[PDB]
Image (cartoon, rainbow, N blue to C red; front, side):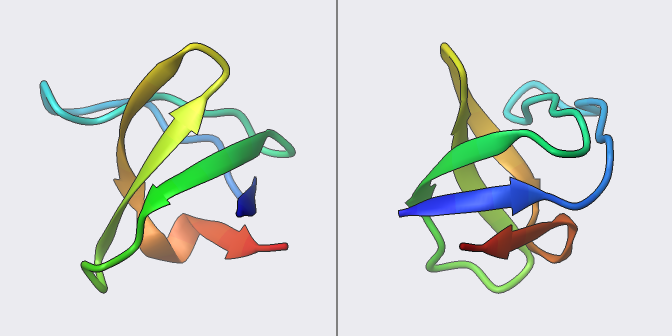
Length: 55
């Protein structure tokens, strides 16, 4: 499934990933309510669940 980046987000921890508003990310794991694992182009990592929207 895909998600839309609602805001820019710069990774702030080793396991996080950076995204730009408007980016279409592949949702890898949404089992956590606060942090979702996504694939941004060729990178994988966590971003705040609230900053993305399921498409």
